[PDB]
Amino acid sequence: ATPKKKLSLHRRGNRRVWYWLKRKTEVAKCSYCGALSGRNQMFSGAAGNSACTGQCVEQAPTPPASSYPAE
Amino acid sequence: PRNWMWYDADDEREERRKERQRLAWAMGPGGGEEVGAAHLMDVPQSMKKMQRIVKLVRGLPYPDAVAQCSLVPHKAARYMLQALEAAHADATEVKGLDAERLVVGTVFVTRGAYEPGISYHSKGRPGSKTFHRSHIRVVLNQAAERPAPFARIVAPLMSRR
Amino acid sequence: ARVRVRLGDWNRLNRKWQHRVSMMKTMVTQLLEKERIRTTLAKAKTLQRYADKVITLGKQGTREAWSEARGIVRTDRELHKLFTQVALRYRERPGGFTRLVRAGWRERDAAPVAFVELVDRPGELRPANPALQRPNPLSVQAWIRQQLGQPAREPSPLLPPSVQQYLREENRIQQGR
Amino acid sequence: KRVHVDRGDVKVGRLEGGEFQVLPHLRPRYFVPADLDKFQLKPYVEV
Amino acid sequence: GNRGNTYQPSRRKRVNRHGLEKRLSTPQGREVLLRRLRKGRWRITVDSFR
Amino acid sequence: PFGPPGAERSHDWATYARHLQLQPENRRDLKRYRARFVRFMQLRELDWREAFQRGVAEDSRVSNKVARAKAEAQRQDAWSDYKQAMWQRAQL
RNA sequence: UACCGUACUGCAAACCGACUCAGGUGGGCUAGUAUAUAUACUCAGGCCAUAGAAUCAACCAUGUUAAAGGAACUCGGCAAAAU
RNA sequence: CAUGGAAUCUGUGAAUUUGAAAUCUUCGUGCAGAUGCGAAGGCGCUGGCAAGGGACGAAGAGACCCUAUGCAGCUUCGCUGG
RNA sequence: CUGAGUUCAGACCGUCGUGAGACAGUUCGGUUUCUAUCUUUGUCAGCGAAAGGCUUGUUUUGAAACGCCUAUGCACAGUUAG
RNA sequence: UAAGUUUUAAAAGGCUAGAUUGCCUACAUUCAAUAACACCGAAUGACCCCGACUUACAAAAAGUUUAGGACUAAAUUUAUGA
Ligand SMILES: [Mg+2]
Ligand SMILES: [Mg+2]
Ligand SMILES: [Mg+2]
Ligand SMILES: [Mg+2]
Ligand SMILES: [Mg+2]
Ligand SMILES: [Mg+2]
Ligand SMILES: [Mg+2]
Ligand SMILES: [Mg+2]
Ligand SMILES: [Mg+2]
Ligand SMILES: [Mg+2]
Ligand SMILES: [Mg+2]
Ligand SMILES: [Mg+2]
Ligand SMILES: [Mg+2]
Ligand SMILES: [Mg+2]
Ligand SMILES: [Mg+2]
Ligand SMILES: [Mg+2]
Ligand SMILES: [Zn+2]
């Protein structure tokens, strides 16, 4: 329950292999604003993106709907 | 090459120290050709916590190094982004190096000055809650060719019909 | 220690069950008051299942459904909205009244974050699909739905012309009693 | 602020039945001069 | 019974034990004060102030 | 505040002298009696505050209880207009 | 009709314990069901800041339930259950 | 089965210990129970999560015995003292 | 893991003793610390790159892919080791 | 899950390495943060997941269904008889 000797620099490096992080092999890049994120995640202005210019979504027309606004 | 001198001795000592390390950076490890670099001092993170992120950007090109820093939730990745952005700013606007060919050819973490504290173990024994610091040295070389981007760029969720 | 994910059941969300049901009732009330809320993935998935249950209960429109929703749904300003605007909006939709879009991680604890919103509304982020898809009577699906016992299930207006000949009658008004 | 220390005041009376009585001869009197207006000596001497 | 809290603060007892007047009341207290002076202590007693 | 408008301009030592005069056996411990009277004065100042808080809370309860029913009446009378509008346009 | 106290805290992150310490710290006031200052829910009032986020590890702590038996367990029905 | 640790991630962030280590098994030998010597054999390398047989694990230069020009307190028909 | 008995500190009974005390004589009561460094062991995982020459079997505008032996990878895997 | 239900021969049975043989349009992202659901699964020529409807002759795990998420395409179907 106690180290009997002092760990060497080589043994410490070998033991610390679990602590290292793996590199990610894919990234989703917005061509305008240069943002970077995963392909399954929104990274536009609604999420955190202060560089968003809205050019990330290139078409959004939806004028017609009809309903009862409850007031 | 600075025929002038400062007025106070402190400024003169600092300027001579700066020129000595600019000598040591040239004709040493690398040096030679024109290099954009940055030194981010006193990052409020441990050396192991920074070394967790620094092993990801070692040897990568600049855009996928920014990608590797921007794809993790770690606190150290924001400081690594700050250092890489400072090095990129020096390389592109202070120097005249071409972008999209910069490779992160040298990045390492050195020790900072610690702030010693105290932790209160049981049975009256003292402890520690030392606040660790570290420094970042980033050197961006310019390659002879634009390199392989190492991470495939895919379209986001926004780019959808 | 009971298996909830991997054996289709409700999430535990790090909470006791009475706290868990109360938090879901608060979130479904918030989801229909402001139609898009942002939260962690586990609460987002649990909210999506609970929203389908609550919206169908509002779609029944019965007195027992109102009584059950009166305890489930807190605001009362939005109990009216669930039984009137939401019920008329999704009157013909066979489930799936909510979509989930992941939005990265939050700063305080690096937890995954999802956007959860009601579909088919002005201000949604993806075009909806029609709940019904009128069939071609000259295709294979219609003949399979004639030989087998399936209804027509066509898209309809809120009041079709099949009630027009009853409501036009001046002897079927009763004067309003 | 801890032990009720008495400051450097001059006492003007004494308690007889718990009601303090200020003795009128111990009330403060200031012998100010007749006029300090258009008096020909100022606090400053010219250099 | 947890120990360590023997110091129960009280201004009356502090001044009545280690104050100037109990030090001056006895001869050996006066040599205690005299060797406090000979050492050079800035605070002579626990109740000194100005 | 929290006490009546007649609470100022009224010396409370009339109470002290009154209950010291008509009960001649309160003169045994006069200092204890005065301590009890001063304690009564602070306690009465607290009871005024408590009565004010309870009165304001009981007013606010029925005010919100009325306003909620007014809001539901407005919502139902807004829904009925829409429903009759739909059936009327089905008529036309 | 002077002089001193009057901020803030005071079962506590502000006092005594090296600590933002699960410990120790005196007196007083109080509404309903209701009936005792006990017990369950609640009034006035206060609080949900000092690690967060999901999930089915083993194992540990604390509990609920358990067929047929029932101290056969164990140094000792200790511990639980039971009245 | 329930609650809370433990296990995963993010953030804060100790200590006991430490001659240097790149520390295999068995048998023999040996300051007399060997990771380090001899003979034979085995072993891609490094870890996480677990169990603790070994490292005569760690934690006290006093558990017990003996010794001191050793101390200390106590006892008495030990000795001497007003 | 226990501490039931073999080390104490409290007390009683009996034996011996002038007494402080002794009893391996009977009794009642009397702190079991440790988060695993590496040696084993269970189990779950990561690392251990290649392309070699084709004089390319062919083509002109020894570089480019094509066709070969096996090199990795993957699958079934000795009448095949342990 | 056992207190329940099956099976426990000569050699049977398991684990690790593997001569060979065969094949190759294989950079490894998403469907929920602990795939152990799922690699003997799926990603729109998709019922993989989720929701909706029905079932007391399942006191509820199957059947229909692309409503929602695994994005995606046109000059003969916004698309499988999923
Ligand atoms: Mg558990
Ligand atoms: Mg409860
Ligand atoms: Mg006590
Ligand atoms: Mg002390
Ligand atoms: Mg307390
Ligand atoms: Mg302490
Ligand atoms: Mg405390
Ligand atoms: Mg309560
Ligand atoms: Mg909290
Ligand atoms: Mg029974
Ligand atoms: Mg837990
Ligand atoms: Mg040996
Ligand atoms: Mg292992
Ligand atoms: Mg371990
Ligand atoms: Mg001797
Ligand atoms: Mg869809
Ligand atoms: Zn953008």
Image (spheres, coloured by chain):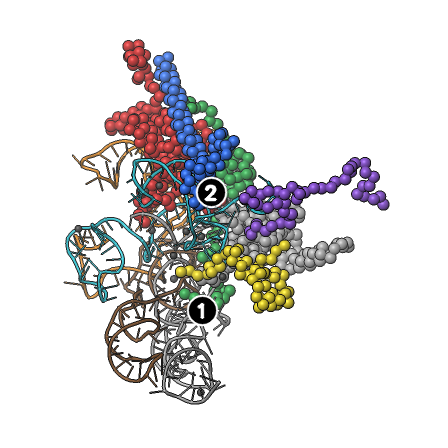
Chain colours: A green, C red, D purple, E yellow, F blue, G cyan, I brown, J orange
Q: Residue at x 48, y 36 (%)?
A: F13
- Camera sees residue B54: no
x%, y% of residue J3?
Answer: 18, 55
Q: Nearer the viewer, residue C57 or C137?
A: C57
> What x and y, as percent, mark residue B69?
52, 48
- Identify the residue position indicated by label 2 in the image: F34
Give the residue type at disc 1.
Lys
Task: For marks 1 and 2, give the one nearer the viewer.
Answer: 2
- Name the chain letter of the residue that bears numbered label 2: F
Q: Position of residue F32 (x, y in %)?
A: 45, 45
Q: CA distance from mark 1 to mark 2?
A: 76 Å
Mark carried by residue A4: 1
Q: Chain of mark 1?
A: A
The N terminus of chain B lies in which quarter of the figure?
bottom right
Name the residue at 54% across, 37% down: A52
Density class for disc 2 (Cα within 10 Å; few <14, some 14-19, many ≥20) is few
Residue C137 seen in this snapshot: yes
Give whichever of C25, D3 is nearer the camera: D3
Q: Is residue B3 left or right of residue C78?
A: right
Residue B74 to residue F54: above or below: below
